[PDB]
Image: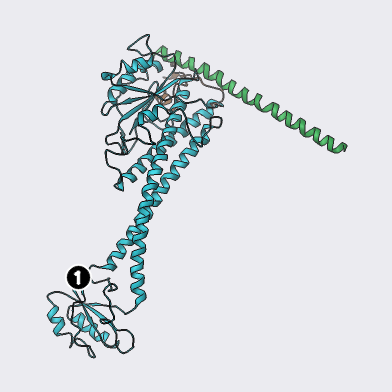
Chain colours: A green, B cyan, C brown
Amino acid sequence: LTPNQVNDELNKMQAFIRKEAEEKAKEIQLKADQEYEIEKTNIVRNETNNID
Amino acid sequence: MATALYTANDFILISLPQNAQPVTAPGSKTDSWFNETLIGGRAFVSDFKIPEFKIGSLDTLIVESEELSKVDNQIGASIGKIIEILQGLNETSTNAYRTLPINNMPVPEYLENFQWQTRKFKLDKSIKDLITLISNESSQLDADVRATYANYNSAKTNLAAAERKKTGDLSVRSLHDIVKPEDFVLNSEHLTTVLVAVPKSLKSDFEKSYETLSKNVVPASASVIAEDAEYVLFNVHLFKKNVQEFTTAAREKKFIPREFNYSEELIDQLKKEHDSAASLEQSLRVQLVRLAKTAYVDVFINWFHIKALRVYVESVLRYGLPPHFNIKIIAVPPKNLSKCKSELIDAFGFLGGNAFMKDKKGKINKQDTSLHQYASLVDTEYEPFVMYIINL
Amino acid sequence: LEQILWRVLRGNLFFKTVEIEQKNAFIVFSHGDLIIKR
């Protein structure tokens, strides 16, 4: 029934709302280059094997 | 409070941000407010901060907080079970193993120097696998001491079963420790051995009626070869066919007949069973003492690391922004946690909110429901900041 | 009591608001987009 608890709750909810999106974007940006590098290596390996 | 706390000091784990201040001292640090503004001026503050772990989202932090609270309660019950198992052996009194140095260092010095140091843990992995591995290691350590105590109870039950065959009332006991080659002859089918248990008052009636008790008896056998606390043991030699008439006259005489046969394997197995049960219980107690001590130490270290990780996860989940906070452990004296809990809760109660703060002191636990634990999955007490009650 | 149960079972990760209606009470909560299941 106090405004300071709602202001502190919104002030924590904003930082948690930003930290969740940053925590997801760091994971997706961490995995995407490794997956693209793995597929880019495998396709070149299969193409070199077919060429030989 | 605690089931294993007799004369041990109490500690309160509190967590707050690095930019917070109390309500009874504006413009002062929390360390100076805890040291100087403490109740009675004897409040001891120690470092309890640890390194931050990788967090993916709040959904994994809520499940890690609930699993950290359930693993903290299971580790707290497993520490009290190993403490009660070690106290039941008579190896630790009510003023030892609760107020002495554990891990080769004191509780305040080891708790102040606890900076997330482990020998099987890492700082780059998930905290859920470390908390589940610590809870599984503490549960296996308590289960090993419980299995050793159950094996010691089975060895004590085997020794108590061998104690009834070793001596006592002549109803199930057989003579296997006072047998000789001059009182029981079983080398031929003509003569045999029959035991007759008679009372102290009926000794003259059994000695006088021993010749008329059955036909084909051996005289001069009325002697006290064994003695009990409710009857006397006598030896009588006769044929196998006269055992029915001697047992019928012994049952009609109000005597107690004993069925015994001359055999060395029965006395050898009867003595070897009591010797193997006594050696098995004697080895099981010595193994259960060291297993209970090592399981108590590993359950204490795993309970401390699980309590620090649960306090950091509860402070990070309850606090939100910023990600870093000031987490420390305050050492309080015995019978003084109510004033420090009411002063710390009243001073730090305005940080969370004015509608969720209430006056409370100490830690009151119950058998129907453990209160004052700060559970995030079950119904319990809640405060504006992170507050944990630990009773040693 | 719902705000006390939500604060005791979820911490300070929600909003406590009340609106008068015609009786009924208008409530509104705020949280993350990935915590809709919890």
Q: Looking at the picture, how far across and down is residue B189, in whole percent?
A: 33, 88
Q: Is residue A44 above or below residue B281?
A: above
Quarter holding the C terminus of chain B is: top left
Q: In this view, does B220 lie above or below B21?
A: below
Q: Looking at the picture, how far across and down is residue B391, in whole percent?
A: 33, 32
Considering every residue shown, the one lying at the far top of the view is: B27
> Residue, x 39% and y 20% (percent of image)?
B384
Three-letter amino acid code at disc 1?
Asp
Q: Looking at the picture, how far across and down is residue B353, in whole percent?
A: 39, 16
Q: Looking at the picture, how far across and down is residue B358, in whole percent?
A: 33, 21
Residue C37 in view here: no
Between B176 and A49, the residue placed more toward the observer is B176
Q: Is residue B303 above or below residue B253?
A: above
Question: Disc 1 marks which residue?
Answer: B228
Quarter holding the N terminus of chain B is: top left
Relative side of B210 to B343, left or right: left
Please tell me in which quadrant of the rendered image residue B211 appears: bottom left
Considering every residue shown, the one lying at the far right of the view is: A51
> Residue, x 27% and y 40% (percent of image)?
B94
| Helix, strand or loop status at disc 1 | loop
